Length: 173
Length: 173
Image (cartoon, rainbow over all chains, first blue to last red; front, side, top):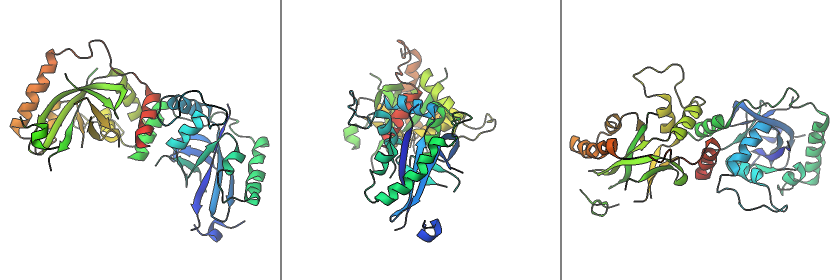
């Protein structure tokens, strides 16, 4: 299935730049729920405004659940969508998990900042601050994924629609 | 299936007592979502502290979805539960839809006050204010449900696990 990319800062500097260090892939899960692994971190770049992260949501099971929940919400602009507008799944994710939360152990899409898209370039271009050199640092990293073994043992997602509901309620609670 | 009862104030007086009036059944839905009708209002009593409502969640489909989402959350005290403790479904509902919201058109279990139980008496006894006369006023009303036709045309719920997730995200959004 086609992945969804996500980007955003895991921390602004205004963790210290030197600490985060100014210059193996962490999995991506839902609200720090290990049973809800949906992808992996593709890149991390320390920039002027902070620590920027970019990940890939690859789980076919998680993505299918999102697609179905999206077809049933007022968060998505219904009616056919034109090729010039972000798709339904992208828009729903932007509404359900608007943030990124670091633990590095892993990164969690947080439901309670994060930009979602079908292309890392487009995603990165959604953040004005990031300079070409920044984008280039991010690109060199995620381009490695094309010849990196991920999801080889299969879909990393170990939950279902029922679990995501519980997970959502738990986080909000 | 065994119903779950819910009670709580729809408004405190400290809507005016005279307005609400100091002295056909409204359906119960999730976050004002007509596709998420899960039961009906069984009674409404104007009391000292305000307008108190008591409803019944009867939908077998909604209840089954809740049961499954409950078996997967940190909101529920896992391990076998003893007969002296509120069951898993009751505890999950108390966490996911902690409030009641009036529209009378209908009442919505709101996710973002409401006490859930398997017995209206127990539920009502969870509110100190309510006096015996109050409880008696509430009882005379819900006792009519035993010979009132409800869910006759079937389960009133028109959604699924995917829809509840959308509904939850929508409300929180």
